[PDB]
RNA sequence: UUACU
């Protein structure tokens, strides 16, 4: 009844203090309580603080509730509910009853969003305030019904739990359930008990299966009694009764995996938890002191001002950490020595973002063009290029307050992070470069996520497969808060003690000079010789201001009480990595110091996610597992608490028993909140294809997820709205209505542009250049249908084969023709979609933005940028890029260096807008592109394709099944890899994952910005190989177009020589390692599966090209694979084309 | 005052850096043309690039000035941890 | 030089360094100032940064790179006819001399040459700039000290007005020494502060104040309590702490010294609070001042409230730094306590005992001790375990936001409407930052006080005062901006009011 | 190298710690020559080192290409040594001569033969105390002074340009002033 | 209106 008739406003729900300075501290219901739309209203006049409160709470209910990824809010909810009709063939599924009962008012929807006026405007004022989130919850549960994670009757238990959370505060109730409702599997894995699992080898192939009995040990059975009492009262009793059946009924290790992913989607809707950030400043970034204070170092040296210069620890928590870390200061001082930092400054001051500043009065006195550029980091350094060597540059930015950026995640609460300007970014940079070189030194300073596939988990898959191990995986809780200034100092000694042994001259606005230094236990100042790294680090360490200051529309300027970690500085990933590495490894020196063993194996720290691995008896490991907790407990950290036998998590990826569990709900399909790089474009479908491939091994039914991505691809992503002008509006309508319907829109006073939106037909959802989405089986002429395209289908030039696949490829080889059926492509509408491809709207909108800005104003700005750096002979990289192109062939833009000085400026002209005068000459150029290509169209076929038209013929004799398939027969090595499914059989028939390929690719991206999926496109690596394979004697010349160092040159060359077995540059295909986790990279593994009669081997690369033909058609047609071995026949022009 | 070597080196270091005798450039020619990429030399190019280190201007001027400086603190070698296992390990002997 | 001494001559006059009247170095100092008019133009031409500073810095510093399409290399070509114009056998050289007033006044185009020069650095003793170095000694006016021993003639010590200037160290009047002793035509350096060499418990301690010898009393050999109030407002004790000056210490000698310059890195942090007090945007700005227990700041920032409120036209009030400890002892027991502002300030300083001085007092007993000389007999790790025991009664008031906790006290005092717009809290120990609320401006006060000497002073100090200074120094490192109490009195004045 | 007497210091009556002040300049001034007699010494070293790595490769039967790409690297150090020995033996050697005549560079450093040299250990003896040696391993680093980096010869040989290797740009070889290293001394 | 790895 809190949803069917909600209460009134109750203004004690968002109270204030005695003053109107901030909200009342310790207030509950910090998020948007469900109160029934009508009741908020302004009463009183535009001042008197509380008016700005009710106006901004209106911004919470009307603006911060919608975040629709592709379409509007209603088109997206219809996309599940239509797809959920088509798949289950009926309408007796009970999700639509929640669509009917939660909102139905008989004339029109209860609420819509404006887009142009940007708010959700209501049409029933009596409906609940919280309902625009319940679109996305009904969206997500139907995504989970379609995924196969939840059945229909389970989604009843889901939806009742969500509406029960909505009685008082829909997210505040959810964040308390979030901890309890997924910690329960460790009981169910205990109860299952003896469970038969695969095991892995050192080099991650499956070598065996064993039955290893999961009974978690005696001391975590004492954590079951404390936790199940909290399960009973904090949860809804039907959601509780669903859990208590999953403890008792579960019989296999596969069976707990069924309930766990399904109970996880009952606690999440994927909605990003958005309120106004004044409410979450108290919750997220307020510093907590968990119990202990951390004491200070003995300061050994101090300069003329009494501040820390050199310092050492005395019997604390830090002395444990510097027992491990201070050994590295003699080596890192030769790696932090041998970079020249001014160079590495301009490469880290890439990624254009903000400076804090709004430039100011001097935005006028730099120019009106560079006024509008003035957001990027690379531009705000260019405007103040003159000030870079003066030491008063950093002094005038201590005066500048740090502004609170907010960004939110899928399940964490609304979180804030500090957007530092260029000078507060400068002091943190030398602690970033010092703490970076511990990564190459110590494995356990660990994994960056360049693999995407199994190598990000190939560590965790191995140690869980082993015997006599307990695994702990620690999050500290909140690790921005906890880092008081004293705990921050343990990283400061390590950054100092490297910089003394090192020799860095000048660094920036410093120089190695002769300072007065107090030497503790001397009386009297004695002048040491300090280098610039030393000076910079001391100043930054001394000076540190931590507070974030957010300007409010309610309040004046709220400022966080400092002492947190301002997590944007430069070292926000190293300061929590180098610290926790010193505390846990330093423990096994201190435990070895007083007669106890260590008994700890490899530990992987990506800050803050600690994950260590132990071995021995069940008593020895626990004596160590307490001290890793207790020293982190006495470091001032709130470790939450996690450990188990056979359970381990890292980077939000669960590994258990030697199997991979998914966390499917974290990829929310239909909530973005980015306000940056929004596509309703070709690029909007790439944002679907990348997220559809995120969920292919987190799903129990990938065929159903292809059904869901199709209709949301169809219904939502269908309409591209374009503002023409009137005279051209007439013929823009007439030309495009010839092929596919274009909507027309009602005419305009006194803006002189009519809108009009084209309708982008369903074939464009399948095109090679448009939507690269895998298809359903079409009809040929007779018609015996095509193969159903599965989830493992690779993208780029392969979707152009689907055009030839409709034309009966087997038939074509019969008549010896490259000819094509224009009838069948025009009938479905394939011909009307490749026109929309050839119109090329996207770079045309980029061309007009590239047309408007004067390159003279850019060049004066960018010549001043290369004054800070190298100094000279960034010119030799521009010379190397231009010498390569005119002698040979085009090496394109983003990659080579000084163009990627110029390209880093460009993005603010890309940012700062489409607006209308530029938009009127969009339509003048596009209509010229329209009337040329509409004047006649036929499907343009290229000489560069013969090179499909090959078709496989099934035979009567079966394959072998690769003996690791018996081991992963049981139990449930991933979610979709259940026994007798498509992904299991592909891991059986296609088989394997090599270590040899994606170690070198894991070696490539350590050059070039690693922390995520890194899917194989990599415009250094493909462009360098097309020169390496066919062409290279030139390959000396474009390495200095990279400005690749001699070490960096060595990485790439070893990957080029290994990428010469497979495959072809001439036939393009792209998949992602997120798409095929355990499936093989190599087309070598598929040549075992297809014989080629060896009169077809007809060119020097032609063995290596036929492998990709064998590689893809197994992955494309895996739902129609009996386990027969197919055989290849070819068109003789395909024989004729590769001869050359 | 055994820090007196720190002065006499620093006077001699300030002479070498003021003479403009060695200027470090940003072009590396450790290997001839198209032996870098040549597969058989993959064992050799790793040994050279591990030893060779970026030419900081501050310590090339120090090594010249240490040659005629008075030695008061007894110098000692950086602990070179090599194996002399492969025949690509002659790079350490050519270094000496 | 970095700044030329003929177009900008008064800055060298502020250091005691007067320009020699108008030869191979008189001709060279005109040659260097001609480059600055060329250099400054060039970094106009393209704002600011003169382009290719490497070939620039290999011309002034090194007699090198004669150069003759073009406009790129135009400013190089115009300059190679300018430095090969005057015949030098080597370069000109730089001369930063290591001073936050001098280093801040270096123009932008000189600082871009510092990366590629190896410049000559002249180490300041305390300031003055101290006069060796064929640059500083052949260019202008090696001076002559004029203490009480070298009296009273210029013919006696063989001085000349074109080579040597005179530093008044008599204690006599300035005007007579160039009247009857014959020092007319001899120009005199002007110093407006003074340097005091005190006696100490540990040795000779040299501190300076930026007051002249007339502006305060104390000469020669008066004690430390005479005009103590002016020394706290304006002094730096340039010595490694523990310096060890005491209330029984006297003066050895006085010489006029250069007025020291405040801290461009520590002027601007304090300038945030002196902006947030002015603007009507920021509700209830807060200044947080950390120091040791014996820095003597409750007697100091009681009049800095009196200097800010008279300049701002507002009402400020400092919370007097122990008002958690005085107040929690009074109402440990009381279920609803009064969080009012007028109740807090009518409670402390001094007669109400602190709560931590109850807790510390009980604790010292348990490891039984009551004498300060008995505390010296204890040593470090046996001491430090006592400090660790002392912490656990700290964290019980810092961890949660209970109704008697520290977080609730500094909140409701700061919010509730009876309080002043802009309170100044002061904290003893670091990691009170999660409790004081809410600010962007936390400074760190280092006064002219060996604080552990003032705790054996205190004169009802005992071990309870001295154990807690030691406990708080274990919790307070210098991880914030040191603020040096004359600099807060300096920044009020600089700020531009309405 | 050779052994140059300090004729400019003794005529200037500078303090020296020897009877004959003799510093060891590392290599001879080599004007007017076509073949550089310091560069051709490094020819006969690589020609000796080519046969040492030849025996080690053929005793342990490695590739024909790995032995060729080793010896193609040994004569790439030949080419780079010829290009810079014109600038060492003309412009570095006149700096080691004039740094030897400075005031505070008073000890001898080297005397030709590695087989016999030890630095002359003076001490400050005392009949009523211990003797304090001058040269003494006490590990008192001056922040990088006692540790000696042998990887400094790779930037010297390869990635540095010299004011005589560049001849073809106009350079005007820098002769520094006497007064800075005199006034500090 | 918008941070780093
Ligand atoms: C130039 O032009 C342009 C474009 O086109 C636009 C867009 O629009 P759209 O968005 O497309 O729409 P949509 O979304 O499609 O829609 P739907 O969803 O389909 O449905 C609808 C709805 O809607 C609404 N509406 C609402 N509101 C609010 C509105 C509307 N319409 C209109 N027209 N307007 C508005 O406002 C309803 O209701 C319904 O329901 O846009 C454009 N743009 C715009 N603006 C701008 C742009 N650009 C740039 N700039 C600017 N300013
Ligand atoms: O955008 C981001 C996201 C995350 N981080 C990372 O967040 C870390 C600090 O965040 P924590 O990981 O410590 O938060 P918490 O887990 O204690 O919060 P709860 O789950 O308990 O609710 C930092 O160490 C950092 O590396 C960022 O710096 N930026
Ligand atoms: Mg965490
Ligand atoms: Mg985390």
Image (cartoon, coloured by chain):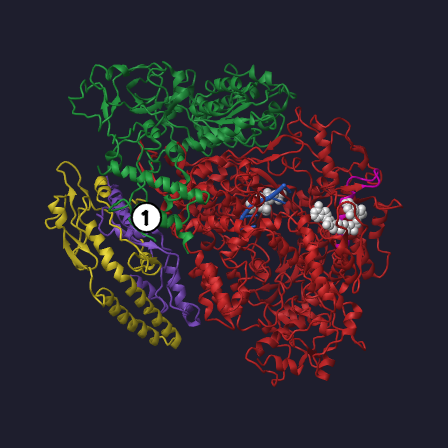
* The magenta stretch spans residue A250: no
The tint chain C carries is green
Q: Position of residue A1092 (x, y in %)?
A: 63, 81
Image coords of residue C267 (percent x, y): 46, 29
Q: Does any portion of residue D25 appear in the rendered image?
A: yes
Q: Colour of chain D?
A: yellow
Image hue for chain B? purple
- Identify the secondary structure beneath mark 1: helix
Q: Which chain is blue?
A: E
Chain A image colour: red
Front residue of this view, candidates A535 and A921:
A921
Please give the residue where the numbered disc 1 appears in the rendered image: C81
Would residue A638 be visible to someone looking at this image? no
Which chain's residue wears label 1? C
Is residue A138 part of the magenta span, yes or no? yes
- Front-lying residue, A190 or A915: A915
Q: In which image quadrant can residue C239 be found?
A: top left
- x 28%, y 58%: residue: D164
Magenta segment: A122-143
Q: The N terminus of chain A lies in which quarter of the figure?
A: top right
């Amino acid at each position: 009844n809190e949803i069917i008739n909600p209460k009134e406003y109750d203004p004690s729900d968002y109270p204030l203090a005695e003053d109107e300075s901030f909200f009342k501290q310790g207030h509950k219901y910090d998020y948007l309580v469900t109160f029934r739309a009508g009741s908020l209203t302004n009463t009183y006049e535009p001042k008197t603080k509380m008016y700005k409160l009710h106006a901004a709470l209106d911004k919470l209910m009307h603006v911060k509730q919608r975040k629709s990824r592709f379409a509007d809010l209603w088109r997206e909810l219809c996309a599940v509910i239509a797809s959920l009709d088509v798949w289950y063939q009926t309408t007796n599924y009970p999700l639509r009853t929640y669509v009917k009962l939660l909102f139905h008012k008989g004339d029109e929807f209860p609420f819509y969003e404006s887009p142009s006026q940007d708010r959700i405007i209501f049409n029933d004022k009596s409906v609940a305030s919280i309902l625009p989130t319940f679109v996305y919850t009904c969206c997500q549960v139907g995504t989970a019904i379609m995924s196969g994670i939840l059945t229909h009757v389970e989604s009843i238990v889901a939806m009742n739990h969500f509406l029960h959370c909505a009685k008082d505060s829909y997210i505040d109730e959810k964040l308390k359930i979030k901890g309890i409702g997924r910690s329960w599997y460790q009981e169910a894995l205990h109860n299952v008990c003896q469970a038969t699992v695969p095991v892995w080898s050192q080099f991650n192939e499956v070598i065996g299966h064993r039955t290893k009995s999961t009974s978690e040990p005696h001391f975590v059975s004492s954590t079951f009694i404390s936790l199940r009492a909290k399960r009973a009262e904090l949860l809804y009793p039907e959601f509780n009764a669903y859990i208590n059946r999953a403890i008792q009924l579960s019989k296999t290790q596969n069976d707990v995996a069924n309930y766990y992913a399904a109970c996880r989607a009952m606690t999440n809707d994927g909605t990003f938890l958005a309120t106004l950030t004044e409410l979450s400043l108290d919750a997220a970034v307020f510093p907590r002191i968990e119990q202990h204070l951390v004491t200070r170092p003995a300061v050994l040296m101090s300069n003329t001002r009494h501040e820390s210069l050199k310092q050492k620890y005395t019997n604390g928590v830090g002395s444990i950490a510097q027992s491990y870390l201070s050994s590295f200061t003699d080596e890192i001082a030769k790696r932090v020595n041998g970079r020249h930092h001014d160079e590495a400054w301009l490469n880290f001051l890439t990624t254009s973002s903000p400076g804090r500043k709004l430039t100011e009065i001097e935005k006028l006195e730099v120019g009106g063009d560079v006024a509008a550029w003035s957001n990027s980091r690379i531009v705000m350094q260019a405007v103040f290029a003159r000030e870079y060597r003066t030491p008063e540059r950093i002094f005038k930015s201590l005066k500048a307050p740090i502004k609170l950026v907010e960004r939110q995640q899928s399940d964490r609460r609304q979180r804030a992070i500090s957007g530092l300007d260029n000078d507060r970014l400068f002091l943190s940079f030398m602690p970033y470069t010092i703490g970076k070189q511990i990564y190459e030194l110590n494995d356990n300073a660990a994994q960056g996520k360049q693999a995407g596939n199994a190598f990000d988990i190939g560590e965790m898959l191995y140690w869980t497969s082993q015997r006599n191990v307990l695994l702990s995986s620690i999050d500290v809780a909140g690790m921005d808060a906890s880092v008081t200034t004293n705990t921050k100092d343990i990283y400061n000694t390590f950054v100092l003690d490297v910089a003394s042994k090192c020799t860095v001259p000048r660094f920036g606005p410093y120089y190695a000079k002769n300072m007065e230094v107090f030497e503790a236990g001397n009386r009297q100042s004695q002048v040491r010789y300090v280098n610039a790294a030393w000076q910079a680090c001391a100043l930054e360490a001394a000076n540190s201001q931590t507070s974030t200051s957010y300007e409010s529309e309610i309040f004046g300027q709220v400022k966080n009480a400092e002492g947190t970690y301002p997590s944007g500085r430069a070292d926000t990933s190293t300061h929590h990595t180098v610290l926790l590495q010193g505390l846990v490894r330093g423990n096994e020196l201190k435990r070895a110091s007083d007669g106890k063993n260590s008994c700890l194996a490899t530990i992987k720290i990506l800050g803050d996610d600690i994950m260590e691995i132990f071995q021995g008896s069940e008593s020895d490991t626990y004596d160590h597992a307490v001290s890793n907790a207790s020293i982190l407990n006495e470091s001032g950290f709130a470790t939450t608490a996690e450990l188990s036998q056979n359970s381990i998590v890292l980077l939000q990826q669960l590994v258990v028993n030697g199997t991979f569990w998914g966390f499917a709900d974290r990829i929310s399909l239909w909530t973005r909140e980015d306000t940056k790089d929004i596509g309703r474009l070709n690029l909007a479908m790439m944002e679907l294809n990348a997220l559809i491939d995120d969920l292919v091994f987190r799903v129990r039914r990938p065929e159903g997820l292809k059904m869901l991505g199709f209709f949301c691809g169809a219904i939502c992503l269908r309409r591209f709205t374009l503002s023409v002008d009137n005279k051209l509006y007439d013929s823009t309508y007439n030309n495009l209505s010839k092929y596919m319907t274009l909507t027309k829109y009602d005419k305009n006073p006194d803006s002189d542009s009519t809108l009009m939106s084209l309708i982008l037909p369903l074939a464009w959802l399948f095109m090679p250049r448009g939507g690269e989405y895998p298809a359903y089986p079409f009809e040929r002429r007779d018609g015996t249908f095509t193969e159903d395209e599965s989830m493992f289908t690779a993208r780029g030039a392969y979707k152009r084969r689907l055009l030839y696949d409709v034309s009966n490829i087997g038939e074509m080889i019969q008549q010896n023709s490259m000819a094509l059926d224009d009838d069948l492509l025009h009938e479905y509408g394939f011909t009307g979609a490749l026109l929309l491809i050839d119109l090329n709207i996207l770079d045309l909108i980029d061309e007009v933005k590239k047309e408007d800005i004067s390159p003279v104003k850019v060049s004066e700005l960018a010549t001043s940028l290369e004054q800070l750096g190298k100094l000279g002979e960034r010119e030799k990289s521009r010379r190397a890029a231009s010498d390569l192109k005119i002698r040979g062939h085009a090496l394109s833009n983003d990659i080579v260096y000084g163009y990627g000085l110029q390209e880093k400026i460009q993005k603010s002209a890309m940012a700062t807008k489409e607006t209308t005068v530029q938009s009127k000459r969009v339509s003048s150029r596009l209509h010229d592109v329209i009337v040329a290509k509409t004047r006649d169209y036929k499907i343009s076929t290229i000489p560069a394709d013969a090179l499909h038209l090959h078709e496989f013929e099934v035979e009567d004799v079966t394959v072998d099944l690769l003996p690791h398939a018996k081991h992963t027969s049981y139990s449930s090595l991933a979610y979709n890899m259940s026994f007798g499914s498509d992904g299991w059989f592909a891991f059986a028939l296609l088989g394997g994952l090599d270590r040899s390929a994606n170690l070198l690719r894991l070696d490539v991206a350590s050059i070039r910005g690693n922390y995520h999926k890194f899917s194989y496109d990599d415009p250094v690596f493909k462009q360098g190989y097309k020169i390496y394979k066919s062409d290279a004697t030139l390959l000396n010349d474009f390495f200095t177009a990279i400005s690749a160092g001699p070490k960096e040159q060595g990485i790439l060359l070893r990957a080029f020589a290994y990428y010469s077995l497979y495959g072809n540059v001439e036939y393009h295909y792209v998949l992602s390692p997120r798409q095929l986790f355990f499936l093989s990279d190599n087309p070598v593994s598929a040549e075992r599966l297809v014989r080629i009669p060896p009169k077809y081997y007809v060119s020097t690369q032609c063995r290596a090209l036929y492998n990709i033909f064998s590689y893809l058609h197994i992955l494309r047609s895996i739902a129609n694979n009996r386990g027969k071995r197919l055989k290849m026949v070819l068109h003789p022009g395909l024989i004729a084309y590769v001869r050359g | 005052y055994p820090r007196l070597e720190g002065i006499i080196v620093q006077i001699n270091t300030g002479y070498v850096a003021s003479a403009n005798v060695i200027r470090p450039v940003s072009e590396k020619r450790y290997f001839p043309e198209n032996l870098e990429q040549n597969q058989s030399a993959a064992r050799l190019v790793s040994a050279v690039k591990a030893r060779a280190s970026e030419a900081d201007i501050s310590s090339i001027h120090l090594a010249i000035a240490r040659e005629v400086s008075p030695m008061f603190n007894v110098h000692e070698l950086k602990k070179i941890a090599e194996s002399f296992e492969d025949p690509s390990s002659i790079v350490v002997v050519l270094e000496f | 030089f970095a700044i030329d001494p003929l177009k900008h001559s008064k800055l060298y006059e502020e250091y005691g360094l007067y320009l020699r009247p108008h030869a191979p170095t008189i001709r060279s100092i005109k040659y260097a100032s001609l480059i600055h008019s060329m250099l400054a133009e060039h970094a106009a031409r393209h704002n600011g940064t003169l382009i290719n500073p490497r070939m620039y810095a290999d011309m002034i510093t090194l007699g090198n790179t004669k150069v003759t399409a073009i406009v790129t290399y135009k400013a190089l070509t115009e300059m190679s006819t300018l430095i090969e114009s005057f015949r030098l056998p080597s370069g000109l050289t730089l001369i930063i001399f290591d001073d936050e007033k001098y280093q801040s006044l270096i123009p932008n185009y000189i600082n871009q040459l510092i990366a590629y020069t190896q410049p000559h650095i002249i180490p300041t003793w305390q300031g003055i700039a101290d006069f060796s170095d064929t640059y500083l000694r052949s260019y202008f006016k090696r001076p002559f000290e004029l203490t009480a021993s070298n009296l009273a003639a210029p013919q006696k010590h063989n001085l000349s007005p074109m080579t040597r200037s005179i530093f008044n160290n008599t204690g006599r009047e300035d005007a007579v020494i160039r009247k009857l002793y014959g020092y007319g035509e001899y120009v005199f350096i002007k110093y407006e502060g003074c340097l005091i060499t005190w006696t100490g418990i540990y040795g000779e301690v040299t501190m300076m104040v930026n007051l002249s010898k007339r502006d305060l009393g104390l000469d020669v050999g008066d004690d430390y309590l005479k005009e103590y109030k002016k020394l706290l407002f304006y002094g730096v004790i340039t010595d490694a702490i523990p310096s060890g000056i005491s209330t029984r210490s006297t003066i050895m000698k006085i010489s006029p010294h250069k007025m020291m310059n405040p801290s461009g890195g520590a002027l601007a942090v304090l300038s945030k609070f002196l902006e947030a007090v002015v603007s009507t945007n920021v509700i209830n700005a807060t200044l947080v001042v950390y120091a040791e227990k014996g820095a003597g700041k409750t007697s100091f920032l009681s009049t800095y409230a009196e200097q800010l409120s008279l300049a701002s036209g507002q009402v400020v009030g400092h919370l007097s730094s122990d008002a958690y400890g005085r107040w929690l002892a009074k109402t440990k027991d009381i279920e609803e306590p009064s969080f009012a502002y007028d109740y807090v300030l009518s409670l402390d300083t001094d007669d109400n005992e602190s709560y931590y001085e109850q807790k510390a007092s009980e604790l010292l007993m348990s490891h039984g001790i009551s004498e300060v000389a008995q505390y010296e007999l204890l040593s470090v790790r046996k001491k430090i375990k006592m400090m660790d025991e002392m912490n656990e009664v700290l964290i019980a008031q810092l961890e949660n936001a209970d109704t008697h906790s520290e977080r609730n006290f500094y909140y409701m005092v700061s919010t509730g409407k009876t309080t002043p717009r802009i309170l100044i809290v002061e904290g003893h120990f670091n990691a009170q930052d999660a409790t004081i609320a809410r600010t962007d401006t936390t400074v760190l006060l280092r006064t002219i006080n060996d604080t552990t000497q003032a705790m054996r002073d205190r004169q009802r100090g005992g071990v309870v005062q001295l154990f807690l200074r030691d406990t708080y120094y274990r919790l307070l490192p210098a991880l914030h901006t040191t603020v040096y109490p004359f600099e807060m009195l300096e920044s009020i004045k600089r700020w531009k009011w309405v | 190298g050779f052994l140059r007497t300090d004729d400019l210091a003794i005529a200037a009556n500078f303090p020296r710690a020897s009877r004959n002040p003799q510093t060891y300049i590392p290599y001879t001034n080599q004007r007017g020559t076509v073949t550089n007699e310091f560069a051709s010494r490094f020819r006969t070293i690589v020609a000796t080192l080519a046969n040492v790595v030849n025996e080690r490769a053929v005793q342990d039967d490695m590739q024909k290409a790995t032995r060729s790409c080793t010896k193609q690297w040994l004569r790439h150090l030949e080419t780079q040594f010829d290009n810079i020995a014109v600038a060492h033996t003309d412009h570095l050697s006149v700096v080691y001569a004039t740094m030897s005549n400075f005031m505070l560079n008073f000890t001898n450093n080297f005397s030709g033969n590695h087989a016999t040299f030890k630095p002359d250990q003076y001490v400050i003896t005392s009949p009523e105390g211990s003797y304090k040696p001058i040269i003494e391993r006490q590990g008192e680093t001056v922040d990088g002074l006692t540790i000696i980096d042998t990887s400094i010869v790779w930037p010297i040989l390869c990635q540095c340009t010299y004011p005589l290797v560049r001849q073809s740009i106009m350079e005007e070889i820098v002769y520094p002033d006497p007064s800075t290293t005199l006034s500090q001394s």
